[PDB]
Length: 174
Ligand SMILES: Nc1ncnc2c1ncn2[C@@H]1O[C@H](COP(=O)(O)OP(=O)(O)OC[C@@H]2C[C@@H](O)CN2)[C@@H](O)[C@H]1O
Ligand code: NA
Image: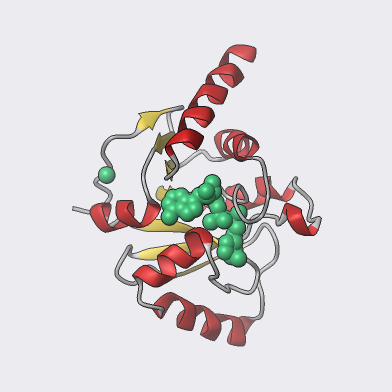
């Protein structure tokens, strides 16, 4: 019922990847945890964050505003667990560094560390879009940091092929 993932490519024992839209995957799989690539104020404008919020008919944004009002912003590299609304049981909002604003790229390791508190997650590549991190570097940090089962949704077919191709070089390099 829950967590019925299909059609993924196995990269390691715990990291999987698929050329798919993350919202479509969540609707098909009804996962326990879906990952949002967030900013510290939980303002869902564009990217994965906008996609998930629209699919919840803006419920995610209202909940986030309420969370922020009570608790204040997240830290870069931090996370919070909120409702997954109609897409998942829970949504893990993770804030990767915004390299375009000069934030420290090493904090991407902190962001993916949050994945290790959940048995299985559907997730995007953190900081690889609006936040300006290299998608390949984001995959490297994911692969090196996450010990739990992470299912990565990469919607662009050209990016998917480049990531898989670059991953092979990473394994044979050392
Ligand atoms: N709907 C999508 N399904 C699967 N993958 C997606 C989807 N939309 C974007 N992506 C990809 O997921 C990766 C992460 O991109 P973003 O969603 O912009 O995340 P990020 O760079 O951490 O920036 C977070 C900001 C925080 C808010 O301002 C809105 N987005 C990139 O490779 C995107 O091309
Ligand atoms: Na699936």
